[PDB]
Amino acid sequence: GHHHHHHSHMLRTYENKEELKAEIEKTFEKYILEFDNIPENLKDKRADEVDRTPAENLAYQVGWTNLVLKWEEDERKGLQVKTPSDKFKWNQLGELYQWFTDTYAHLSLQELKAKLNENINSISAMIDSLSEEELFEPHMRKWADEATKTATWEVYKFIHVNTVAPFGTFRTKIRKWKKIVL
Ligand SMILES: [Br-]
């Protein structure tokens, strides 16, 4: 079911936890830097050949990182987890994305950047909290095995496709937006 994820074709091998954390921080910094000169008054400005506004772009990352953190926190607390979310299934990502916009896009860029920054720090704490086995071997978290229909994904794959991969593709999109609008 997780193959419905839009970055399922951008998987990566990692050597260890440190390599994973370093890549998340590097790609996050390059992505977030692009918003430094985007004014709040243009956060909802839509460019023609770009799907999302700057706020919707940030809202998407806040949305997904909030979900990954929730799956693990809920499991840590002994709960049974529904993925990708309680309201939407893996074949309803389009609706989940609109929910991200409705839930988060109205916030200021400053507030969205603060939330994403906090989430990157929490994801690093999560990586540090799991053994190398829990992170890199299959069948270590019930939430990661929850939707499997074809190939199994280890915890690190879920972290990677929701951080390193979109930070790269959405950085391309926000740069395109700035070239047009600014
Ligand atoms: Br976009």
Image (cartoon, helix red, strand yellow):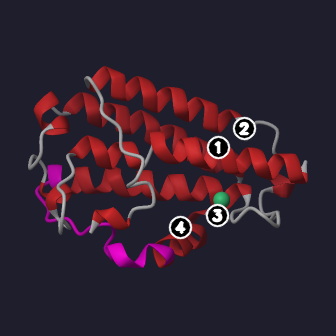
* Gap in angstroms between the C-alphas marked 3 and 1: 17 Å
Residue 85 magenta: yes
On screen, 31 above or below 138?
above
Report how far apart the C-alphas of labels 1 and 2 lie in the structure.
7 Å
In-image side of 49 versus 153 (left or right): right
- Neighbor class of circle 4 (other Cα within 10 Å; few <14, some 14-19, many 20+) is many
- Within 8 Å of ligand 1, the CB of disc 3? no
Question: Looking at the image, is mark 1 or mark 4 earlier in the sequence?
Answer: 4
The answer to the question of whether label 3 and label 4 lie on touching residues, with beta carbons closer than 8 A, is yes
Amino acid type at mark 3:
Ala
Residues in magenta, as a range: 75-94
Q: Which residue is mark 2?
A: 34
Q: Residues within 10 Å of mark 1 (few under 14, many from 20)?
A: many
Q: Give amino acid for label 2.
A: Glu
Residue 96 falls inside the magenta stretch: no
Q: What residue do we see at 15% from left, 59% from top? A: 145
- Ranked by sequence position, the earlier of labels 1 and 2 is 2
Which amino acid, mark 4?
A: Phe
The answer to which of 66 and 89 lies nearer the viewer is: 89
Q: Secondary structure at mark 1?
A: helix
129 relative to 49, above or below: above
